[PDB]
Amino acid sequence: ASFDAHERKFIVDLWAKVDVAQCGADALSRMLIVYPWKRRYFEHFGKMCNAHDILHNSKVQEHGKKVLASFGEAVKHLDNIKGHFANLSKLHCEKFHVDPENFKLLGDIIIIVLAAHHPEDFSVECHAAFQKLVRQVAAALAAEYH
Amino acid sequence: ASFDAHERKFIVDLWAKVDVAQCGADALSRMLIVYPWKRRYFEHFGKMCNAHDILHNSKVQEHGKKVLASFGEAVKHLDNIKGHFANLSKLHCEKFHVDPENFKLLGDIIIIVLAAHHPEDFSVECHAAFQKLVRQVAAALAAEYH
Amino acid sequence: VLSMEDKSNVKAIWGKASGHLEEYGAEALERMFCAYPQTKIYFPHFDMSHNSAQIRAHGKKVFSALHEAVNHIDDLPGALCRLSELHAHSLRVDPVNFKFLAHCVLVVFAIHHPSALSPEIHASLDKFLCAVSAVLTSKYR
Amino acid sequence: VLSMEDKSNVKAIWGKASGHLEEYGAEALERMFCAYPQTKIYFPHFDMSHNSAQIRAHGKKVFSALHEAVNHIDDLPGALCRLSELHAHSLRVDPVNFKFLAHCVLVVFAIHHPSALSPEIHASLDKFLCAVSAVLTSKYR
Ligand code: HEM
Ligand code: HEM
Ligand code: HEM
Ligand code: HEM
């Protein structure tokens, strides 16, 4: 459902404060540490045996920056999230073969990374605005899975 | 994704053989026995303490007939499943407050009920056609959840 | 299964909440009610204001229960036996909701203790809240 | 948790498959591959024909493993210890896939033994296949 004016303002004002490179590397690293089966989807990045390996993997760090910058593009397309992500959704399904249940798990990790970097701003109402965003982005990635 | 000619023919030919009243009562009864938290959504049908109570509950039996006849309408709207179910989806979300993860669980039970009543017909390829249908119907019910 | 290291990890991050069970507990429920408003159907009789007496008192009970769980992390089924009957048998809470409250607990720790909730600690805590959730959803019927 | 009655139930429906472990096992995988084609990425080297030598031999191993599980239904973690390391650590099977194969096992019993898989029996069997799945997904990392 559409974001209201108040949802929009929380989202738009928080995201202008976000360091996308540092939070993206953080979010991607944590998802491979918390849910270790996801490592199989990235077996081409190399060293992913333990959490030290992951935290020190330059390709994991780099990739996290792109994933979050992509996600960040939802903030300019709040009215059109499903349409904006439709090609990516295809790419995940066909080329990377990723089970769509995993998108919801990354979205939760992103909430936790944002909460830790922006505690004064990540209020109860702000957190509800972002949870709705993350639910829409995960749904738009899963949408072209046929 | 669209059903091909072969998917369509499996589906359309099986469903003409189905006893919708008996399979619907069967499917609804089993879902309340296998996943007992679902009983909370129907606390207005009465006696749902044990499985004997459920199997003997006339309102549960009756309701199962409607749910399956509804589902059966997908077979005449294969090209338009998400559009056909959009109001029902609303009704589930707003009026009955049902968590959308539960639609996938009913769909699996329906596969098991059909398999048991039509074993010679429920081949490997037929079962794959029906699994795709059930995945689309569960998705169309969850779709208006905002 | 929780390793010995997971267990050290959970105990140590848990100790940060020691004086703040009501505070952290109340904040987690506030977050669960606001971010997953479908959870409100289980508390029809609650005042849903910020820092409501009813929410403060329930937030305390929840986190007090999670605090004994940490103190009995070897025997979670026995520590949470009565709770599992309440949630699954008497209240018929749909098992999806345990994931929502677990996520909100994690958000509270990240806000209050961002350095302590490192990635490997984050992994242990999440293992412990799945383990607690599994015990509470173990008794349906 | 599996009650005493669930356990009687699982043993009795399991006995119907006793002479048909390869047959039923092969059919369940055929069904999982066809109805959930995303599961095929784990078996790149398999011949995916009907009644393929490779599928018959793997269907047997799976159902033979599930048969010892039934025979040790009190101690599933110990019965499936080595399998849990293979699946979670060495193969990194995404945990959604265990639900797909469990559903296909249930479909095979419904086809071959429709009267025996009554609703209360159906509930016990489904509890046992969730329990087996939980052990096999218990060792990630
Ligand atoms: C917010 C959710 C997500 C977004 C926005 C996202 C975005 C992206 C983007 C932008 C790429 C690069 C596409 C390109 O190569 O041009 C990508 C690649 C990829 N994504 Fe995702 N992704 C998300 C979730 C996930 C999840 C949950 C997984 C796995 C568990 C995953 C696995 C992959 C893999 C394997 C690649 C290919 C990596 C490579 O070969 O470099 N993604 N994703
Ligand atoms: C194939 C999936 C489903 C279909 C086609 C379906 C269809 C229906 C239909 C046609 C009704 C009657 C609507 C009316 O009153 O006009 C209904 C009502 C209802 N459904 Fe569903 N349903 C499905 C799944 C579920 C699931 C999984 C649950 C709960 C776990 C559920 C809970 C309810 C409840 C509580 C009602 C209201 C019952 C009453 O007050 O009589 N449904 N559904
Ligand atoms: C970590 C997970 C949870 C723990 C540790 C927990 C703990 C508790 C405790 C200690 C009580 C009080 C029991 C008593 O006073 O005897 C309780 C009651 C209750 N819990 Fe939970 N709970 C959890 C998850 C949930 C969830 C997810 C829901 C619903 C979405 C929920 C709904 C309830 C309800 C409705 C009550 C009745 C409260 C009342 O009387 O107002 N709980 N829980
Ligand atoms: C009831 C659940 C399951 C049981 C009881 C089971 C049992 C087994 C057994 C007994 C083996 C042979 C191990 C050996 O020879 O030492 C095996 C191997 C394997 N299993 Fe499973 N398994 C199950 C679920 C799954 C699922 C869901 C997948 C993937 C979707 C899977 C993928 C594999 C793969 C890829 C192998 C390697 C087989 C090969 O060498 O070709 N298993 N499993």
Image (spheres, coloured by chain):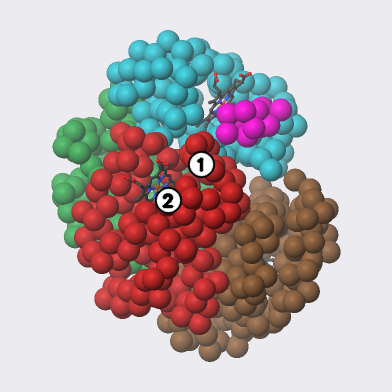
Chain colours: A brown, B cyan, C red, D green
Compared across the picture, whether C45 is left or right of C80 comes to right
Type of amino acid under label 2: His
Q: Residue furthest front?
A: C53
Magenta range is: B87-97
Q: Mark 2 lies on which chain?
A: C
Q: Earlier in the sequence, mark 2 or mark 1?
A: 1
- Residue C58's tag is 2
Q: Where is residue C137 in the image (x, y as percent from the top left)?
A: 35, 46
Q: Do the residues labelled 2 and 1 touch (CB within 8 Å)?
A: yes
| In the rendered image, the vertical position of residue B140 relative to residue D96, given as above or below | above
Ligand 3 within 8 A of label 1's CB?
yes
| In the rendered image, the vertical position of residue C33 relative to residue B105, given as above or below | below
| In the rendered image, the vertical position of residue B22 relative to residue B77, given as above or below | above
Q: How far apart are marks 2 and 1 (CA)?
A: 10 Å
Ligand 3 within 8 A of label 2's CB?
yes
Residue at position x 71%, y 34% from top? B82
Residue at position x 58%, y 29% from top? B96
Q: Main secondary structure of the magenta part?
A: helix
Quadrant into which the C terminus of chain D falls: bottom left
Q: Where is residue A70 in the image (x, y as percent from the top left)?
A: 74, 69
Quadrant hosting residue D127: top left
Quadrant hosting residue A29: bottom right
Q: Where is residue C13 in the image (x, y as percent from the top left)?
A: 39, 75
Quadrant into which the N terminus of chain D falls: top left
Label 1: few (<14), some or many (≥20) within 10 Å?
few
User: Residue B88 colored magenta?
Assistant: yes
